[PDB]
Image (tube, coloured by chain):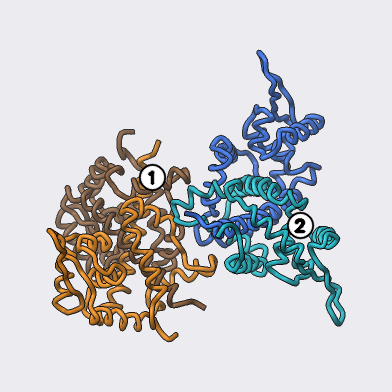
Chain colours: A blue, B cyan, C orange, D brown
Amino acid sequence: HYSIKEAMLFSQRIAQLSKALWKSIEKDWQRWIKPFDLNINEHHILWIAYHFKGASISEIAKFGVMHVSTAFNFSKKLEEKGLLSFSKKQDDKRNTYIELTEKGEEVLMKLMETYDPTKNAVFNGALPLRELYGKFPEILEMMCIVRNIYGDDFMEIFERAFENIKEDFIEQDG
Amino acid sequence: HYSIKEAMLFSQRIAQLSKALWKSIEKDWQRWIKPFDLNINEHHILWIAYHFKGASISEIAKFGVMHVSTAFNFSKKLEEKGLLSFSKKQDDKRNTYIELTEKGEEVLMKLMETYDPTKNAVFNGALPLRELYGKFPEILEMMCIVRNIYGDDFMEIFERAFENIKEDFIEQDG
Amino acid sequence: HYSIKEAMLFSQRIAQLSKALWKSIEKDWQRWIKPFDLNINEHHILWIAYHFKGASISEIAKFGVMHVSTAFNFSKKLEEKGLLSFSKKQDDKRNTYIELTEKGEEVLMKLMETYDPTKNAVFNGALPLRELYGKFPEILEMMCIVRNIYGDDFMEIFERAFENIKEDFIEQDG
Amino acid sequence: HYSIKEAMLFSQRIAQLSKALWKSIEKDWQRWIKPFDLNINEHHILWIAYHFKGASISEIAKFGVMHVSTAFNFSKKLEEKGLLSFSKKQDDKRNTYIELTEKGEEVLMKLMETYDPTKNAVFNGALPLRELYGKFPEILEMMCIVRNIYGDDFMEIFERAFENIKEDFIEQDG
């Protein structure tokens, strides 16, 4: 009931649009986090550690869209800075668990003190759509596919990010 | 008139959603193109060469969301396969121009003969939204930001991709 | 799992938005059809008769969002003009069926010769959203609810309207 | 730059969709308000009176999508019930102003005690889209046209309706 043509059209559409979105976010994300000598995957774990305090590196991998192997290496380089701590559970656990540090939290805070959304590209690009809608675009069409792929357990990172950001101290002036 | 809080919420929203979209497309794109020993940026140039027959590597970079330096190296490794050809313009041109080859076109065709949209993730993930809308999601909210960033000249790749795909031979059976 | 508050908010939202949409379409629809001394429900039947050539007044009621009683009276006043014809089926049929006339078709055509979308309000109001999307808004969110209510058989009027309009003679110049 | 064909397609699309939306809301709105012997335009004024305490009948007409003449007659039949009160301003005012009564407020409250969103059609029809989006559809595409027509001053009724509904007593149990 579905044409291969309309499929290829869809795929070429979203593949070009997704690469434009990640590559532009990469540039603004890296410039924001490079003054602390970190990469986007390491920072992802540092924010995942704030939003979920104690999580297996396997969960860090799922929420981080990383390989388990990849998340291990960056988490270990993060402990070796003191920005993160490691824990092992009782009984019999193969899993290795992860928490943040006061040095790690403070690094996130001084990054928050330097958050200029003006410099970020997608922010300015979404200012037109915000003025017509009254609020930032909620891109529900995209959000539906991602849940329908990664799972509802993956999507819960948005909820906990929002609620923790809602109860947040000293973002900037005021 | 805009809260820094609603900005951070937006940024964390789209940054998590964009990374999920590119990483899942990467895996399905690479598996599709790896039987020919190519990467996603090289294939991008091979499709850009079909949709725009003669283009500067600088335009290949803009449409490809690549650095000019990066597009040069992959285009040169593509000529050294015979999948692509190079040209230089008259008068005085610093620019180096690019065309496809019959070997390069045929490689795209045998990849088209192996296009199973079932294996691609975002395809199956968009089947729910297609049934409710009658047709594949057009994600216009995203498409507006990207144009408002990369430029209308960048966006013309979708038009020429659609029209060339509409006039396409032997995708699969029928 | 659902708040009565978010329900009331939704209802007050769509009830105010729907009344604004119908009342503004009423004014532009009536001004367009009043030079022929017809109402919006009568014209609806005249277009339903073009898109579905022979239909029961009960189907005219479903597609017309009219009562069966209401559709009868207007269809009868339409036959008594010669803009429409009536038929009765074989065997044993309670139903009364309906077709268009050459006088009725020509009335639709001279209305088509007078279609100025500039005067229609929603047209100009949708010009902003069309420029950002490249094409007229497809309001899929609304279209999903209506199908989920009236039925898929009701929705088929859009398909046959589009395809018949695609194969249409002398709309205006060219 | 715009086809008359794509215009007619758009108009037939939204005209059929808007009539389906108003007619279905009419039936559920009237059944909800008929036990108090009121019509949808009268109830509209009674809610406009709650959301804007003292407003000219001309503003009631704009927010109510009514004629000034029509809003006068229903407001006068509302005062003659004691559900509403009238006032005249100082200096020199042609305008006649309007406020609610305790009898009028209590009528709205006992209607709120009888609000079953299950019986309302569009509510159940929007339950599918809510489950995929996590929240009720916000139909921003429609909301943009209406603002681009009726004006931003008209749209402020949604803001004051939301904020007043957010600070509301005894909707139902809890």
Image position of B80 (left or right of C49): right
Can residue B151 be spotted in the picture? yes
SS category of the residue bearing label 1: helix
Q: Position of residue D57 (x, y in %)?
A: 27, 64
Q: Which residue is mark 2?
A: B42
Residue C169: image quadrant is bottom left
Residue C107: image quadrant is bottom left
Q: Label 1 vs label 2: CA separation?
A: 45 Å
Res. D127 mark: 1
Residue C83: image quadrant is bottom left
In the image, C60 versus D1, the foreground residue is C60
| Amino acid found under the numbered disc labelled 2 | Glu
Tell me the crowding category of disc 2: few under 14, some 14 to 19, or many 20 or more residues within 10 angstroms, Cα based.
many
Image position of C132 (left or right of D58): right
Name which residue lies at 50% across and 55% down.
A2
Q: Position of residue C87 (x, y in %)?
A: 16, 69
In the image, A148 versus D69, the foreground residue is A148
Tell me the mark number nearer the camera, choosing from 1 and 2: 2
